[PDB]
Length: 200
Length: 200
Ligand SMILES: N[C@@H](CCC(=O)N[C@@H](CS)C(=O)NCC(=O)O)C(=O)O
Ligand SMILES: N[C@@H](CCC(=O)N[C@@H](CS)C(=O)NCC(=O)O)C(=O)O
Ligand SMILES: O=C(O)/C(O)=C/C=C/C(=O)c1ccccc1
Ligand SMILES: O=C(O)/C(O)=C/C=C/C(=O)c1ccccc1
Picture 1: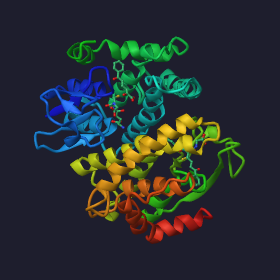
Picture 2: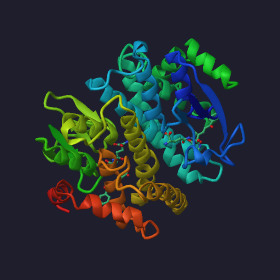
Picture 3: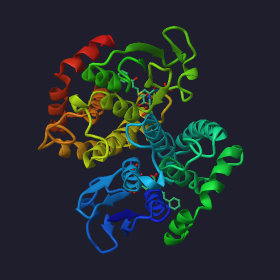
């Protein structure tokens, strides 16, 4: 099993998930520019859209999109309880949060990283983010994790996205529950092992 | 079961899925400007983020995010095969496609429907879409649907987002396989019933 990744990128979410699952896998780094792997192979042969993550199975079969990948990972080690059982209502609730993180958080961070983007663009996105962060913050007043008392792959994804705040000049202090969350997920061994393996 | 919708918005996706599934439900229109439902209820009481779709279950529980909703819907009628079975590889592959449509397609249409979006934002997004729609056109070149020969809720979601192109002046002429896909899906009785039901 292979995870195509780039240090600090959103591929850190499946990376943390794999560790939390206690699975073994190979990291393959990708040059996000020439779209070539560390071993000099063409990545657009693996993922046509040219982004990370991509999970490749022993099979040769592949999966892209974080929310899909992290669900595949969790379902390999149900004992770890990293996602609700499929067919339970809480699994749809997991998927809801995964899509929220991806479409409402992650995609809003994207143009803040972009040097080309105007200041009128960035400021509109920053206002939307503040609002969406407020919503996530309120959720994390109810319980230490997005779905309650057990860590799920949705918390892992959220931890990764929130960790980008430092690079786009977002202070998380206005939301005590988001800082409490960061701290709580930040100090897990699997998470640390993942940051270490990525040089962070 | 209630579906909160706005005519022609992304909620048309669960709408079509519900009809494909043959399920009983009540459409509840939402004024996206004033954020009031048809009954005059404050819609933020229902979805804290303020957007459609939202699925309200018989028992009062709610689900947001298109990709979560359409999976719940499909899982209600497994005989109809609107999604591959949970735990199968092809179900992760559906979630990949659903997250792709949401984060890579839908979210890039969003600024185009905005008057207050700068022409810089719009030009960038149109370019992202040109590339991303190319990837989907290639996917739909030698197979009728996203997952192969079987229509799924991913195809329904794609069909709805593609339908937005006329309203924001996106020409799909460079992608004949996408127009072919539109005619393949748009010709289904549940799709045409939903269009009619939304007053379109
Ligand atoms: N929709 C994709 C987005 C993946 C994505 O935005 N990956 C970024 C890193 S966080 C990337 O590889 N860079 C963008 C690119 O070069 O295309 C997903 O959720 O997996
Ligand atoms: N992340 C949400 C996005 C939903 C969404 O962007 N809905 C739009 C219509 S397509 C909407 O209700 N408009 C936003 C608003 O009215 O403020 C999802 O995938 O369901
Ligand atoms: O969301 C995007 O468009 C995107 O490419 C995000 C990438 C983020 C990073 O690679 C990254 C690396 C180190 C630290 C923070 C962020
Ligand atoms: O993508 C969005 O965030 C968004 O607000 C999409 C809106 C879709 C529509 O309401 C719509 C309605 C009729 C025709 C085309 C589009």
